[PDB]
Length: 127
Ligand SMILES: O=C1NC(=O)C(c2cccc(Cl)c2)=C1Nc1ccc(O)c(Cl)c1
Image (cartoon, rainbow, N blue to C red; front, side):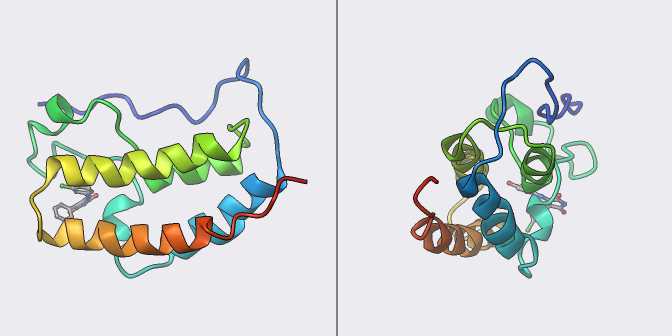
């Protein structure tokens, strides 16, 4: 079982914005999660070949990862904050769908998600 193409991070005809909320999602949210000791499994698309997870992309039909999110934020791919928040939530949910409760990777996702929730709680009002 092979890897799919990664999610796109560039699409010139998709309209985009740089908003204060999106800036916060990069400068505070992504940066906080990216530097965490448990970030590493989430910094790039899951390589199902190297990890010997041939069923991964049979089960996970909407892959997402922080490498992709980082590129989307840096390349101003998004129209609004909700699109980016959805990407983080997709990433966490994929982990919980694929893995078993208590697995290391689930504990890692939970630690990142707790921080994510704390930061999104203080998402600034749109300017
Ligand atoms: O990119 C990766 N390199 C690794 O060794 C892993 C990985 C695989 C199994 C357990 C743990 Cl804690 C990490 C990655 N990421 C990953 C990210 C989410 C997942 O659900 C799974 Cl199974 C793996």
